[PDB]
Image (cartoon, rainbow over all chains, first blue to last red; front, side, top):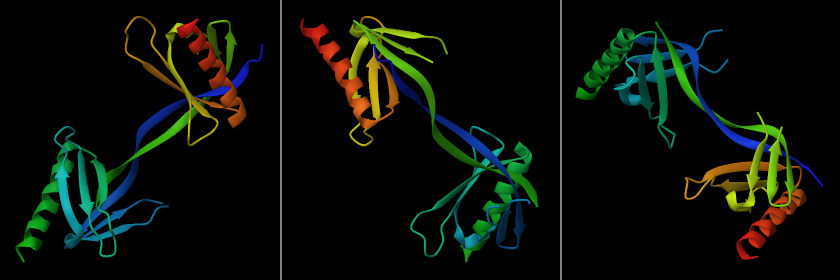
Length: 102
Length: 97
């Protein structure tokens, strides 16, 4: 009559949202947590893609290459609002167009 | 300066304690509410090749319903093997005897 002690294993998956500030300074983009992770300082030359989500108006992503790095870092964000999303993506798309013209 | 939220997908395994008991052709998994299986409902029971304490049991309620997949962790690789063996023996005697 041995009953065995066992654990059922259940995959959980969820999406955490961590507050940042995103600042655009000329061709630099600074992605800054308030006060533990480090601030990210990107140059427009590093951005390979920047896109407002088609499903969720408030979502956008910025993909980034760096010089000694194999992979693309893929940074997904949610803006405070659909309108702030479109502003941030447009401003970055225009900086990237301008930079790439050269 | 815009206020934005970095979205980060996080994934992990939640482990829920149960007891597993076998009585004749029935399997009881209890901590939720008690779950009872007949051996005819079991499609497959397999020990992990990577993690010796892990096993899984696949189940079909009725007829040709979609298979449901349950994953479990035992106290030890020995006890995982013992559970897997006992349930395989039962399923085999059911299919053949």
